[PDB]
Image (cartoon, rainbow, N blue to C red):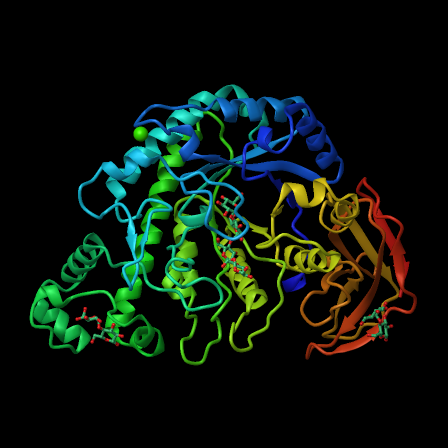
Length: 516
Ligand SMILES: OC[C@H]1O[C@H](O[C@H]2[C@H](O)[C@@H](O)[C@@](O)(O[C@H]3[C@H](O)[C@@H](O)[C@@H](O[C@H]4[C@H](O)[C@@H](O)[C@@H](O)O[C@@H]4CO)O[C@@H]3CO)O[C@@H]2CO)[C@H](O)[C@@H](O)[C@@H]1O
Ligand SMILES: OC[C@H]1O[C@H](O[C@H]2[C@H](O)[C@@H](O)[C@H](O)O[C@@H]2CO)[C@H](O)[C@@H](O)[C@@H]1O
Ligand SMILES: OC[C@H]1O[C@H](O[C@H]2[C@H](O)[C@@H](O)[C@H](O)O[C@@H]2CO)[C@H](O)[C@@H](O)[C@@H]1O
Ligand SMILES: [Ca+2]
């Protein structure tokens, strides 16, 4: 892995349940057998969307957690674990969606203004999830839902390994900037979603709070606004993305725009910990979307991410740290393209995100954005998961591997692995002052023969005059590896004579000793 490290010892593989209720896909008894099959293939737990639309459909405080309890019961019967997602967003309308569960229709009647939903640059209304600006409504509703959910599920604490929160559309903390109705679906630029009167008012008040008066606003932005009502979000999204973002106005607008998501993150994290820490005491997390298109568009740099709300990932992740929420990035199986017209750089995106997360000490989890039908995508996921310190990987989705033994087997081999500590010892290494020693191998867990950025470092043992390292390896998987030497300048000086192997890596911690 990067930084002379290896795979994360806490790595776990997860399986996404279907979007629709289990009975609409199969039966509970078969489902229990599926779970056992999943566990046998290296899956630690099943993640599942519990839709707000299903749990509080009829009206405020009219809960129904029976499906969830029933699901949990079967999970318990299979001797499995589960990760509930309190899906406060609509199922249907997003990529891969095979469902139709809008959030409770009554919620939209909690306000007479337009504070609850989103409106795009062109007026497209979106009601997939509550507008995070309506923090008062969010605090109440989410607080009540989380609290009631905790009580109803308390007797199933034993099978709940983690709890996920939904920070926006598709269960991700972002704005609904890429949708078919708004004409912003991949791979087009996204449209900003701050055009409801309420959003314009909030931005206006935020700006005036920051500078005090319009006169000071005009001084800071170098503008000549005639009235406070002239303080508005971008009137021309395209022009803003081309050059407007560079101005002090642009920086302020984006700070506010992303800031809303950061505050929302802190709010839901607070509400979740209050409702769950005592009852379950398990990690809590939220998701960030991989908006990889328009990444390197020369004309509109990161033209899809900024409208989605992603302007500064470092700053965004800090909010997750403050809220004590683990992060899941949802797009690891893709390769960089960076070519017209999509300007897609998903791999670069994931690496940057993973790097920030690791630096900040944020538990990082990953998912594949689209269904995987080939082993190559699994290898791409593995390269990212095992070289960028991911603590977990969740496969979308259930059916793809449950009904494809071939694919299921590839997954077990490459991603359904159990990490195990092992000591690697290499003797008679002809190193000189300044040299460092590393090992690299065939599997992703070993850096896939990369010597530049993914090798695993070994350390000299002056007591035994050899080089050693405690490495995390995939249990019961065959491996091939070789130690090699890097000079002070970082140049690879030489390699170990014979290629080593472990067929397979022992389940119990031990050591592998070989000579250079
Ligand atoms: O069961 C959990 C949730 O499952 C669904 O949400 C998934 C979604 O299906 C999945 O695609 C994803 O990854 O999120 C991002 C993704 O990271 C982005 O890349 C992008 O997807 C685009 C593709 O990358 C691109 O190649 C092309 O296909 O266009 C895609 C969409 O424009 O956008 C999505 C955001 O939706 O993760 C989520 C979260 O698990 C389901 O929708 C959701 O309701 C469930 O909660
Ligand atoms: O709120 C002030 C004005 O903001 C926008 O205008 C921005 C524009 O979005 C940006 O691309 C450019 O670089 O700067 C101007 C401000 O000088 C709105 O479009 C205007 O209607 C607002 O008055
Ligand atoms: O680059 C992929 C191959 O890496 C190694 O091959 C090394 C070899 O170990 C070393 O002794 C020699 O000097 O250089 C080659 C090429 O870098 C693995 O041993 C191979 O299995 C990989 O395919
Ligand atoms: Ca309520």
